[PDB]
Image 1 (cartoon, rainbow, N blue to C red):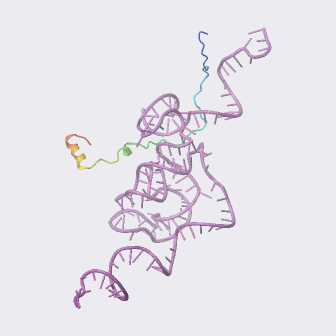
Image 2: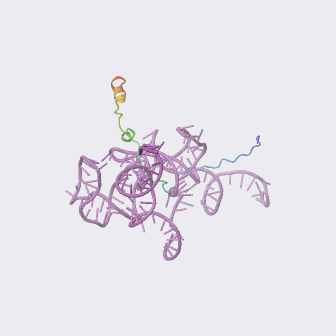
Image 3: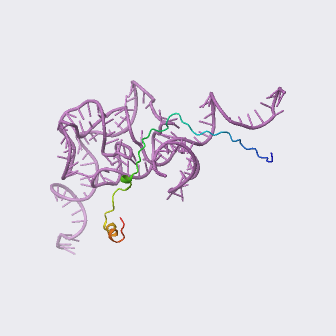
Length: 56
RNA sequence: AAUAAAAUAUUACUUUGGAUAGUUUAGUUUCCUGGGCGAUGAAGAACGCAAUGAAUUGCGAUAAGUGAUAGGAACAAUAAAAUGUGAAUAUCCAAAAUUUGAAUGCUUGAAAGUAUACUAAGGUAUAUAUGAUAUUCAAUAUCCA
């Protein structure tokens, strides 16, 4: 057989097919654009960047 | 010999100190009833959440609280807004339940991370050992054409 090593044969490998859902959690994203940004920084240091550097 | 400054002695008032008396939402012991945790993720740990919070308490991205059921007019340190079209308050209930931790895809030091499959993100599942069933195999191990 031109080789000495014996390795485990490649038997068939079915994919997982659960009979009931593993979780009933609602499909809701808890990180949206309203929760990502809390509030703008309102310090005078942050207020100086708006006019010149065009940054918020 | 002499003076009473210091010294000494007693009482009253004051002070330093916190004894004594009165008091107790705290303990100790005995007894009665249970002894009701966890892969459906426990106990423990961390972080976060109050209009003004640092601790503590309560809670978990629905945050000092949501629904339902009882309950019936308060809360307060200050100001707000809501409220008999139901405020406080209570619960073996319902929803929701961050990161970890037996911790369980792999890694984990104070580590930031990262793979595959299913349903760009998000969410699930994938540790080790093990019982039953199904399926694909391996070994001439026993026969056997």
